[PDB]
Image (cartoon, rainbow, N blue to C red):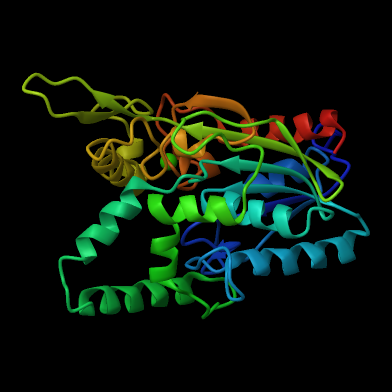
Length: 320
Ligand SMILES: [Ca+2]
C-alpha cells in the first residue's frame, strides 16, 4: 500500500449501460479497479444503478446515484465525492453535479456518450422496421430480464427502451439542454468546453478521456470501413479470450458507416469530449476502458488500471 491514490474526497465509480456493481454478484464492472485504488490509498465506493434506464426522472439512474452518494458521505463522514463515470455513468455523474453541486468535487467521464451513440440511433432504426411495436416490446422484455438477472441486487427497475432512447444522438442533445455544463462545447463542434465549472457556489473539476481503437479506413469505390488498432490483426488472442473485442469492432464499424468517426465500439470521440480532455488516443474499445473482459485487451491497448490509478493521483494533486 501507499499514498499514491489518497484523495481528499472518496471516489465513486459509476457504471454505464447494462451495468451493476457486480454482474450476477460474481463479476465486477470495474474489474480489479477498486482493489488497485484502495491498494494505493484511495477510498473507493462502487455504485449499483439500473443497467437500463434514463438518467433523469424519478426512476432514473441519476436519482439512484444521488441517493447512493449520500450513503457514502454518511459512511465516510466526508463532505463531497469524486464521481468517476464510465459510458452512461458519466451522464449520470453530470446529473448529480447539476442537481446537488455541493456534494460533488469533480466529474470524470470515461467513454461517455455526451452527444449520444450512433449505434443507439442504429438500434432504434432497426426496431422501427416492425411498425407494430411488438418486436421492440418483446426485445425490451428480454433485455430488462437480462438486467434483472445480472444485477447484484436483482434490480427490477429496468427500462430498456428508455435506456435506448436516452443514448440516441437526438435525445442526448435534449439532455444537454436540460442539464447544460461548461465542460461541454457547442453542439456539433467536436470540441470540449472548460476544465472547471462553478455551479451553486461549488467549483467542480471536469475530466474526460476516450478510447478510439476502432478507426475508419480507406477505400476505392468510396464506402468506408473500420480497423481495430487495439489488436494484432487477425491473430490477436483477445479476439478469442474476450468476445467483446470482435463484437465492439462490428458495432463500431456500423457507427463508422453512419458518420461517427473513430470510436470505441459504442461511443465516438466527439461524443466523449468533456471538460479537460486528457487523451483520446487510447487504443481501447468500449470495455477495455474498464479492464474488461477479465483484464483481456488487445496487444496494443494500454493498461486501463494504471490510467485510472494515475488519475486518482491527479485528483490528489488537484486538491480533491
Ligand atoms: Ca477487452
